[PDB]
Image: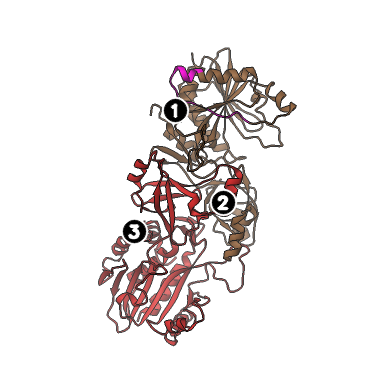
Chain colours: A red, B brown
Amino acid sequence: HHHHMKELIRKLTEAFGPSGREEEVRSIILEELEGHIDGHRIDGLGNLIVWKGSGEKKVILDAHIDEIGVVVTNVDDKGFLTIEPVGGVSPYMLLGKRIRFENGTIGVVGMEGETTEERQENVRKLSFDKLFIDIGANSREEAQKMCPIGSFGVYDSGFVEVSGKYVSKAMDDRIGCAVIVEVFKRIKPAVTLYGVFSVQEEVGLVGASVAGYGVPADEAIAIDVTDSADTPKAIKRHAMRLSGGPALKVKDRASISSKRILENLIEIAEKFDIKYQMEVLTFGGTNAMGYQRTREGIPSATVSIPTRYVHSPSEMIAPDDVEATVDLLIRYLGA
Amino acid sequence: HHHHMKELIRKLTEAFGPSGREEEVRSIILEELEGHIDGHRIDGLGNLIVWKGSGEKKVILDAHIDEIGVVVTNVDDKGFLTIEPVGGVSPYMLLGKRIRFENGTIGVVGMEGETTEERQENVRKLSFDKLFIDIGANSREEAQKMCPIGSFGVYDSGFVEVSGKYVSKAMDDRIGCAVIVEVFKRIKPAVTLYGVFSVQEEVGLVGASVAGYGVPADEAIAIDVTDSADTPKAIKRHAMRLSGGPALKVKDRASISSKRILENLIEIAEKFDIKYQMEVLTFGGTNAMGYQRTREGIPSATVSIPTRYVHSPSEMIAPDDVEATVDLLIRYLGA
């Protein structure tokens, strides 16, 4: 390795930050960036925006700070919790897992069903309303004091090295957050660089990303994860893979200016022998509204870290891909 | 609490001992029993037998030392492991979990399937042959060096306190092992007491439990776990429950001598105000062979610790039930 990002990745991935409660992650980001940013602000949606540099061109790098999890929606007479999903969490991934709550309380996920046929019927068509969380309470009253309705939880799973790979919860998108932090620590920007550590935008709600988080940027580059389809039988040509480098794309039907960002990233990677992969463009439909949506706003591209087991408690990345991503961005955004 | 068993329970439940590889558990048991046993032996099947006392009546206490897990059956060209179950492990409980191998190697369980319909089809009817384990290897050769075919793994999950409950892997039956160890540490036996820490007997193979592990005992008491059916909707009268005390039973159609052991345990519990529950008798069929099987061998009974989430990485017990079990046995087997 040529960066020293392990501890940053451990800290960010282990931090508590389900959608709606990301205070710890923002605080960690600001501590890591102390002395490396010229300023910051937090918008009314909870997006953290930082900046460094004074160059003519304004560039956003945007990674999501929120993670998948659960929210408590009911407490029963014996102290058991009902939950709903926060983000894309499959109930299959939650079965038998331990969940850590904001206040440090640990709970165990169980499933309803007594007989084999009951459990078989349930587990074969698993629904969140068949799950519950046991926090060791013996009554509604004990449980409501520890995890009242509206409490968030995340996986009780942290960071581990798995023969040269890194595994943790919340690679999506704490790994993107780590990339941006590392870029801010290392770069002497030729641009005015904005780092946005954003809350994800629920479908059906107004988000801030289209308006550039109020930053009048010339370019916006999302730093995300993409599924690494290099596991057994999910073996196709042109798949994203671990150790293939950052995955580069734009949206389908992107503007000339957005495509230029992609071409320029490709050129940097080629000139500096940085591994990279060409990802299929983000699908956005085929209608007239979708066409006009890409031709307004800020020219944009996406750079993604290949990740196995996305949305599990054991998301896996190759540290070389992360370092390559940092290197690519520093070369692109530097002198 | 009135015993100090937390550390013993943590140590035993965390120990590596899938069926076929229980060396660490036997070693821990012997270390804990140093100075409290008069002797021991290990039989050809791997059953560890210890003894203390010199009384006329010979009594076995028997708890299983093996835990559920996985065994590696194939290594593919990219380093991914195929597994089969050891013991009663559902593939649903393994999804996204981390597995710890004998040599300390950690792996992540994944499932085959790329599309939503593929994964939905797979996960709705989950089979072990759709799972794999990723140990971070990049080739068959790297993987075979870390986890060759025949390697065992267990849950990568250890002991935690959950508001006054204890949660770990392998309560089934490390909790029974802890009960027996604690009895040996505390008791002045009025009997010759044998502690058997047994390997489970595969259906279809000859085991040693029927012959009393070669001990010519007068009574044999299994110390096991039983499912605690006190979770949401699995709410029936007469259910075993946490904090209801040890669950007491014999086999269906038990002999007069076996039923006497049960009656005598009940009497002890009543005389000493120890909580207990009456569990439905062990089902053994209704035919002539089953009838004669209970009337030979050693008079036997079972004392069980109520446990939630059996066969998950988060098996849960109430420490009061464990202490009550120890207390009951010490009173029964003492002067």
- Binning the other alpha carbons within 10 Å of mark 3 as few (below 14), some (14 to 19) or many (20 upward) gives some
**For the residue marked with disc 1, what is the amino acid?**
Glu
From the viewer's perspective, is the residue at label 2 or at label 1 nearer? 2
**For the residue marked with disc 3, what is the amino acid?**
Arg
x, y (%) of residue B109?
55, 54
Q: Secondary structure at mark 2?
A: helix
Q: Which image quadrant for residue B135?
A: bottom right
Which quadrant does the N terminus of chain A fall into? bottom left
Q: Which image quadrant for residue B55?
A: top right
Q: Find out whether residue B268 is within the magenta segment.
A: yes
Location of residue B127 with respect to A194 vertically, above or below: above
In this figure, which residue is indicated by the disc labeled 3? A21
Disc 2 and disc 3 in contact, CB within 8 angstroms: no
Q: Image check: A312 left or right of B161?
A: right
Which residue appears farthest toward the bottom when viewing the image? A256
Query: Which residue is found at the position 48% from the left and 54% from the top?
Result: A128
x, y (%) of residue B222?
57, 27
Could you give the CA–CA distance between mark 3 and mark 1, rounded to whole angstroms?
A: 40 Å
Location of residue A239 with respect to A15 vertically, above or below: below
Q: Secondary structure at mark 3?
A: loop
Disc 2 and disc 1 in contact, CB within 8 angstroms: no
Q: Image check: B77 left or right of A103?
A: right
**Same-chain check, marks 3 and 1:** no
Question: Mark 1 belongs to which subunit?
Answer: B
In this figure, which residue is indicated by the disc labeled 2? A123
Q: Is residue B91 visible?
A: no
Question: Mark 2 belongs to which subunit?
Answer: A
- Binning the other alpha carbons within 10 Å of mark 2 as few (below 14), some (14 to 19) or many (20 upward) gives many
In this figure, which residue is indicated by the disc labeled 1? B323
Q: Which image quadrant for residue A37?
A: bottom left
The magenta stretch spans which residues? B267-282
